[PDB]
Amino acid sequence: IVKIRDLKEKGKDDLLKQLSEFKKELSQLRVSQQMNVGAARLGRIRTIRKGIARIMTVLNKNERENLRKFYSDKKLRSAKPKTLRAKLTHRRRLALKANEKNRKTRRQLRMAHKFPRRIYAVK
Amino acid sequence: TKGTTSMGQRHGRTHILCRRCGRNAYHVQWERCAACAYPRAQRRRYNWSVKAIKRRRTGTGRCRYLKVVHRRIRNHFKTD
Amino acid sequence: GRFKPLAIKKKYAKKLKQNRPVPYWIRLRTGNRIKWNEKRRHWRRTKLHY
Amino acid sequence: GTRAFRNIFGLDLANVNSLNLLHLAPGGHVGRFIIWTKSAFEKLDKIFGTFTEP
Amino acid sequence: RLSGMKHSAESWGTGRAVARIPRIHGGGTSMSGAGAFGNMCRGGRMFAPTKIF
Amino acid sequence: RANKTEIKKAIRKLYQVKTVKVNTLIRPDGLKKAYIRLSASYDALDTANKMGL
Amino acid sequence: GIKCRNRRKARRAHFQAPSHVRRILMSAPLSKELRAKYNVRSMPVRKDDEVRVKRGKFKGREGRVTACYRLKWVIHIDKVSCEKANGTTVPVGVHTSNVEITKLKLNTRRKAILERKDRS
RNA sequence: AGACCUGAGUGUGGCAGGACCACCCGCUAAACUUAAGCAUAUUACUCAGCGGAGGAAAAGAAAACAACCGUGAUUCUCUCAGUCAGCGGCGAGCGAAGAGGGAUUCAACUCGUUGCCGAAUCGGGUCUUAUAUGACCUCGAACUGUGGCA
RNA sequence: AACCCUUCAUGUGAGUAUUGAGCCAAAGAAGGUGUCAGCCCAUUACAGCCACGGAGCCUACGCGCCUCCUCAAGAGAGUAGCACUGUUUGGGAAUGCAGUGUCAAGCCGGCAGGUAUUUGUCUGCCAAGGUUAAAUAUAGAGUAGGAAGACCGAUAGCGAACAAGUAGCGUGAGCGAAAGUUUGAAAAGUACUUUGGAAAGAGAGUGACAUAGAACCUGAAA
RNA sequence: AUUUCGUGCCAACGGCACUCGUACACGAGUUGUUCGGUCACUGAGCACAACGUUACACCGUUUUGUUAGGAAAG
RNA sequence: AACGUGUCGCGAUGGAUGACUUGGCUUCCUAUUUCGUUGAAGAACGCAGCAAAGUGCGAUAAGUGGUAUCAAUUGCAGAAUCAUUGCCCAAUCUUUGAACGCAAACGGCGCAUGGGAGAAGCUCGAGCCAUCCCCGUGCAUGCCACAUUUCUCAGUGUCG
Ligand SMILES: [Mg+2]
Ligand SMILES: [Mg+2]
Ligand SMILES: [Mg+2]
Ligand SMILES: [Mg+2]
Ligand SMILES: [Mg+2]
Ligand SMILES: [Mg+2]
Ligand SMILES: [Mg+2]
Ligand SMILES: [Mg+2]
Ligand SMILES: [Mg+2]
Ligand SMILES: [Mg+2]
Ligand SMILES: [Mg+2]
Ligand SMILES: [Mg+2]
Ligand SMILES: [Mg+2]
Ligand SMILES: [Mg+2]
Ligand SMILES: [Mg+2]
Ligand SMILES: [Mg+2]
Ligand SMILES: [Mg+2]
Ligand SMILES: [Mg+2]
Ligand code: NA
Ligand code: NA
Ligand code: NA
């Protein structure tokens, strides 16, 4: 068995080694499955499969974290892989940005400043 | 001889399975589907068969991605 | 005959594996409603062609 | 003054303004046991009027 | 508004030794050749369907 | 989806044996079966015992 | 909040409840001695608890809870059993509202619940 | 040899197609049926066919009504009105608008043109915690006119 | 307790039922529990309490600092109009539009004013470029929630209360069912003896009931 | 499209019969440098690109040496 | 006599009726309300200890991760806050399909670039590894902007 809190600190080389041992142990379990096994040995197949998935989860997240840091600069902004960019709906990616939607001309700026909204009340 | 005897003269086949929809409606000789009109980009849709339309529309299958994106919209794309 | 595409061969393989009875332990579950496989197929009754 | 008299099963509450006929004659049959508060009783002359008084 | 009327039934005509009611098309279902569309038929449309107006 | 050349290289890595021939077939249920003949310097019975057969 | 003016909706919510909902629905009253001590009317039942049956064929029987069969809406009590034809002994299910709790298996989480529900 | 005009190839960054289609916008477009027959008429500017959006769409700021003691963008509702308006083998049938009471409403703006200026504009690169309505540079676009003031 | 008499037997499931005492109510609310439940369980409230919250929206146009910014002419041309043809409209000597031909004015301008033409007044507007919330639709759509009904009640109501657009049918476009697992509170789902190759029968046993024995509530007519 | 093989089995099915079975059940079986196909040819023919038409491509042309008002050779 | 007929008690055949109802139908309201080249909708093939259909999922395959709660899941196994349960931020996501390197009753065939394995051979068990083989990425058409340190061209077009 593995714990996700312990796999976090390990390096890539250590994680890649532990993956190979778990895959090898799984292969031996399948061989015994063809023969008669017994209930106890038939169990822990799911335990091994769960441990393999946990190592792959940590490996992928570390890789994606490194790529985000590498492209974390305004210089490239276009070499960044599309899968790393923020995904929204297709319509939301094209609609209009916050700064583009509220653009005002010089005349519009002056008129708004000259005649502002007021709150008055009566009587 | 147009009845029982003529049933023994039917040898080949007009249609095979379709790559886009299945349904065994791909005309072998004409190379097009009678159910989805493949390889035309648009598929068939006629308002004189609303029963046929409701057989093929969205929600009759898996909606593998639509389920994900609908949940993301409900939660206003919460992240990190 | 001898000739068949590999895609067609795979479809026939799936139908072979489907043609089997319901396991006995399924009938003993709480709130079971299945007694026998309703979708059994025989090569002389229904064709399915392909 | 409703809070104390609610939750009592079999007791009905009413407002002297907007009296309901479906409540005053249940099933179409007239004659219902009505308890009047003093303030609501004194308002009947104004709400419905008298003879020779709109 | 569509209840009981979602078939492609039609009358067999006269000369087939059956009543002239419309009958369901097709085969292999035990519904084939059954009466359809009438207020007296099983699974048919009722007489004067109710409306919301 | 594996081919003969990949199967031969995988066998050597897993069990540390040298082969002389690989023959494959696709079973009627969709699985792929392979017959692997080892070199004369390697005992198939000894390898099977180590595997646990 | 299952009960509703819609009988059809209330019954669907009850009989399709998930496992964590069924834990709350399967609750039993506390005994008089426990009520005088913890000042709580009732608590959900759990394994290793001691109960006394109050309604049914087994009246006055006491035992320790062996299982909480949430899929069958019943609990199992030791010494509450029936004999099969072969002589095998099988447990008999009892609804949780027919029993009362006499002893609680205390725990740091269970103690937190009791302090939450303390009326005083 | 060098410009300008017109036109190609490649590279860098982007977009279109398909689905859904109840409601909405644009086109195309019947016959059964009624007229106790039927051809104009009716069904109907409907069904079927093609194209295109949204959370609503379309409409919308007078080349508008009226003829009064005058109203004042659009949309919708009651009513005007099955109309002593009108169309029609004047047959069967069909058929609106202004005004009036309301829902909503701080609802309104600006390109071109005219007059005064004439790159003050745009793209790209760099700097300022910043792909700033900022600054500097730019034989890059733009004088066959981008922008700013009345 | 079944033609009549005698002996010997065997037979009543679970209290939400009845009676007598109480108690709560700012809660009497309708679901569950072996029979009809305010007090067996879950619910029923702020006249509330906790943690989370990256974008967005709202709040002295929320609140500081730096940076920036601000305080005489003309008016849309293959356009409008006119002729012919077609369509459309309640629009009738021609309501709107389309095709082709022809094709303006602005020095007493142009368009509209529901009977055609020429002439003169009066009234109201200023086409041939663009954007724009709210009140409106959802007549076989979606995504999450809610509220219900003088509706149907398994040949009804959606085709589908069930592994239903499934099984099945057709070369294909397409067509398209039947079927409540409703035994019992609980499987306690009949150990064991005997006949039989088996299926089963005869006994025994569980259960309040087995003429509730497994497509098992009730069990009509032909 | 598993009807092939072995072992078992006789409820239903093979319009009579079954101890038999292409029935039912549980397990097995199809091995290629040279065999057939693709790799790798043209034919009767088809119709992507390009162009044209159509209110609308879901239309037309596309082998008589051969696409396209036509700058298609990397 | 038999057959046949009629009435009553009991038993078959058949599945009506009653009582039940997690289903349908109809009306109303509320939202941080509306898919896709960042590869949709649909279609195929797979995944559980015992697993045919259905459900969930995709070689990390009846699930990995985060969060709240805590003792279950159950037919038989089997393990003993960490499971299960509800919700959701981080991920994986086979072959196809608008499907887009070229084709297609083919699990087929390329070009460019980066890796991997390698039982010949070479050099000193190790390092290079030819032929063959496997994997990742790019490569459709059309249209828009740009070549910012301003790319390469063509024309008996106009000038010089
Ligand atoms: Mg014929
Ligand atoms: Mg022939
Ligand atoms: Mg042919
Ligand atoms: Mg075949
Ligand atoms: Mg019906
Ligand atoms: Mg082979
Ligand atoms: Mg489209
Ligand atoms: Mg849409
Ligand atoms: Mg007529
Ligand atoms: Mg007539
Ligand atoms: Mg006629
Ligand atoms: Mg709009
Ligand atoms: Mg009309
Ligand atoms: Mg200008
Ligand atoms: Mg507009
Ligand atoms: Mg039905
Ligand atoms: Mg039906
Ligand atoms: Mg026979
Ligand atoms: Na239409
Ligand atoms: Na004109
Ligand atoms: Na040819």
Image: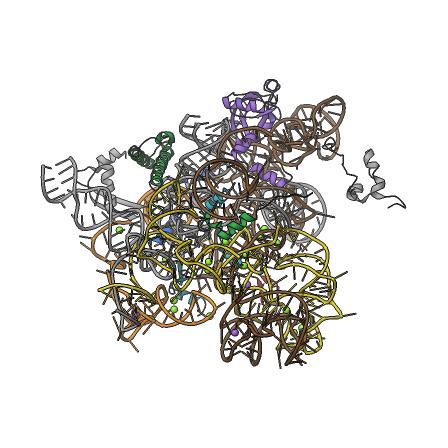
Chain colours: A green, B cyan, C blue, E red, G purple, H yellow, I brown, J orange
Q: Position of residue I151 (x, y in %)?
A: 67, 49
Question: Relative to residue G13, is residue E22 depicted above or below?
Answer: below
Q: Residue at x 54, y 49 (%)?
A: A112
Which image quadrant for residue B34? bottom left
Nearer-the-camera pick, D18 or H57: H57
Name the side, left or right, on which J53 lies relative to I137: left
Question: Relative to residue H133, is residue D8 depicted above or below?
Answer: above
Q: Position of residue H113 (x, y in %)?
A: 49, 65
Q: Position of residue F48 (x, y in %)?
A: 25, 36
Q: Residue at x 83, y 36 (%)?
A: D41
Can the viewer see residue B26? yes
Question: Relative to residue A101, is residue D14 depicted above or below?
Answer: above
Question: Relative to residue J50, is residue A116 depicted above or below?
Answer: above
* The C terminus of chain G lies in quadrant: top right
Nearer-the-camera pick, C25 or D49: D49
Name the side, left or right, on which G4 lies relative to D50: left
Which image quadrant for residue I80? bottom right
Q: Position of residue A30 (x, y in %)?
A: 33, 36
Nearer-the-camera pick, B43 or H33: B43
* The N terminus of chain G lies in quadrant: top right
Q: Residue furthest right?
A: D52
Can the viewer see residue D35? no
Q: Exactly how many numbered labels are in the figure?
A: 0
